[PDB]
Length: 221
Length: 214
Ligand SMILES: [Zn+2]
Ligand SMILES: [Zn+2]
Ligand SMILES: [Zn+2]
Ligand SMILES: [Zn+2]
Ligand SMILES: [Zn+2]
Ligand SMILES: [Zn+2]
Image 1 (spheres, rainbow over the protein chains, first blue to last red):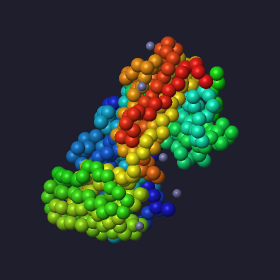
Image 2 (cartoon, helix red, strand yellow):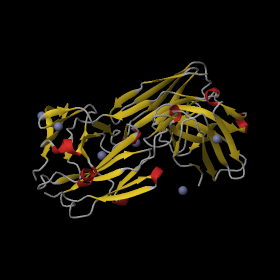
Image 3 (cartoon, chains in turn yellow, orange):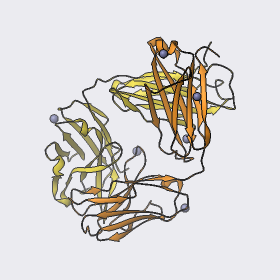
Image 4 (cartoon, chains in turn cyan, brown):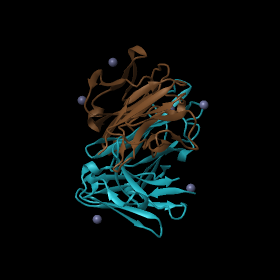
């Protein structure tokens, strides 16, 4: 299989430095190159630099030339991008991409590395099950919730029934307030499914190595 | 630097309709223009390279055209899976330049939200906080307002709202609204209400509960 695989999410302090990696596997011999891209807020993309003999060697966008350093382990085809003088504006998803020469195009992209630049403290989330209001069910369908409150930094992942319950799931983007994120998820199933069958929300917060399961239980008096 | 101007920034389009996105470079870029699609949480994917060259694995309804400074991407017949963001790219000279992007959203019939309200969990109460959560699921269009009321009185402080992207399976939107109170402020009041104002109803859709009723 031909692919680019980037290293995992980061939290780094203002004024420190970070080094992310991108491993290429399965590519034909004698075609190594790598390009690096930044995308803030899931929106605009900009190019940092590249290593590509067919495009003139190692080169940087003037904007990033001071802070960025691109290297490569040629034996393992692993690219590295080191960034220093980190500021909050460097908080972004960083992509690697590899040019495929025939015409040419950027045929392969890494999955992206999320980097958060902040002095705020890592904080594991509280995870709360949300059962419907106390009382008899009114309707043929029921909606349950999971609340993931007060964590830092991103990301978190959430599933229902370890991923086997996927349709009817709405997981909402996290919202940041006072250096803490809050996220929620709703799931909707037929009344004859719950509480007859077990429904659990599973939450992982990688920064704190947290993995938590909260079963949704009918409320009491 | 070579600058790029992409339009429109967003657009609503029906299934089966002809979609055109345009891109203007600040100089002749000799057709070194590529088009990309990007879905939420995913990496960009090339649709077209050298302005009009097509790729295996990209459906034939995508095509590109132009030369000099002016380029366009065409979707001859929109399909559900085409929902997402689109970017042009000049690669005549490095540093390469992406356009600012086009958000493509799909038209559907109007739909009223399904509203559900959730009292604080016993776990959070034992920890000393009290969040009240309201889900507004599967509505259209995107424009919606949520109001919280406590004992009949509107509350604006302590509210966090979050919207999903356009639903990839029914083209609706959903939003979550969380009203966070202290446990003792929660215990000083009886009725908690979230109401949704939307195009689909002249009157708000109201979900409420009482802190002790069952
Ligand atoms: Zn694989
Ligand atoms: Zn360093
Ligand atoms: Zn078709
Ligand atoms: Zn009211
Ligand atoms: Zn949905
Ligand atoms: Zn009060």
